[PDB]
Every structure is written in C-alpha cells, then in structure tokens.
View 1 (cartoon, protein in one colour):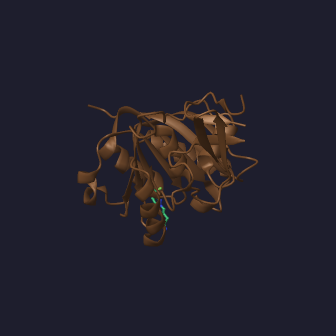
View 2 (tube, rainbow, N blue to C red):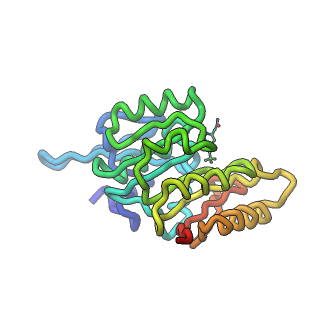
View 3 (tube, helix red, strand yellow):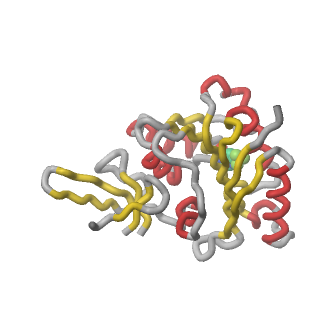
Length: 227
Ligand SMILES: NC(=O)Cc1cn2nc(C(F)(F)F)cc2c(=O)[nH]1
C-alpha cells in the first residue's frame, strides 16, 4: 500500500496528504498524487506544513484535530483557502466549512475555491461583528483560527459564543511575535490561554510548530459555556 491512513481520520501519509475532494485540481501549487489499481482511482493532495499551521500541528504530534467526515467547521481568517481546502477534503461532501475572511482580495480566492467544493461557504465579513452574518451560520462542531493580534482571541470567543455548540472544540494557532513583539513567546502563549479560559474555552493540549514556524503555537480545546 502506497498511501497509509494517519491516526487522524481523513489524513494520510506517504509526506502528509488528504484525499482530494476535487480530483485534478490544485489549490496553491501543491503536488497531487493519484493511485490507480484497476478501475479504482484515488487522488491525494500534498499538505504543506510551512504554509498550513494545522499540518505543522499534525506533524508535531497533536492528539486531536476534531475534524472528521461530516464535521461542521467555522474557520476564521480563511484567507485564500490553503488550510481550508484540506479541512474540506477531510470533512467530505457531507461536512461543512464556513470560511470567514475579511480581505476581499483573499475572499475572491476563497469564492473561487468554493465554486468547486460544495462544502465550503465563503463569508466575506468582519469576524468582529458576527451579528452581520449570523443568519448564514448553522451551529458548528469545531472552530479554527490563527490569532495574530491581542484582540483576536476575544474575537474568536465571540464567534464561539454565537456559533460553537456546547462541548464543541477549537483549534487556534497563536503567532506570538504578531501579538506582542515585546513579550516572550511563552508569556504570549500563557496570556492567550488565559484569555481562552476566561471565555470558557478550555485548552486540552498545546504545542509549538518548530521546525515549520518560530514562536507559533497551536492550542486544542473544548468549549464549555455556562447555562
Ligand atoms: N487581512 C486580514 O484582516 C487578515 C484576517 C485576520 N483575521 N483574524 C481573524 C480572527 F482570528 F480574529 F478570527 C479573522 C480574520 C480574517 O478574516 N482576516
């Protein structure tokens, strides 16, 4: 066998690859590996950990990623769809990925990606004001975000309070240099974990992303709002 399933469901390994929901198409120039044995054919896409914090996290040995076939996902800061494309591969045609991006430039890449992928919903909106787009968002199982400013963990939490089910999960990368360049990476990470806790987003694991990123963490946890 030439592509083995990874511990994480929907993730495969040769290095890290996902099953291409759109056979024949690359999203960001990634290699595509197709394996045929008779009439059976399956195409995978290379998942670059120097571009995608999530792939770096999986390679780094993260225990859970909480996306699987059928999962409903809210991705804040979807940019041009790099990481979202692979989340879309994993959740498959019965899952759903809401891809929120403020940038209109990035948004056009996202809409283009979503033309081919029925499970992506581009939402070209400011995640600071979820009320503007709340009527489009069915309640999700998992939220993803890259936090790069000192206000963004709260912005993620306001979206969790609006859209994330009780007992759903979050996967949040943290770019310490962008949050506070005058603080140590460790102090930024502790401060962001504390901001999470104060919003009932309870971390369950965390890791840094060396060698792919410097002073970049990924935190995985569970949302436990009060009644
Ligand atoms: N040009 C930009 O504004 C990039 C960007 C950052 N960004 N951060 C979040 C947050 F993490 F807060 F959820 C959501 C977004 C997003 O839509 N776009």
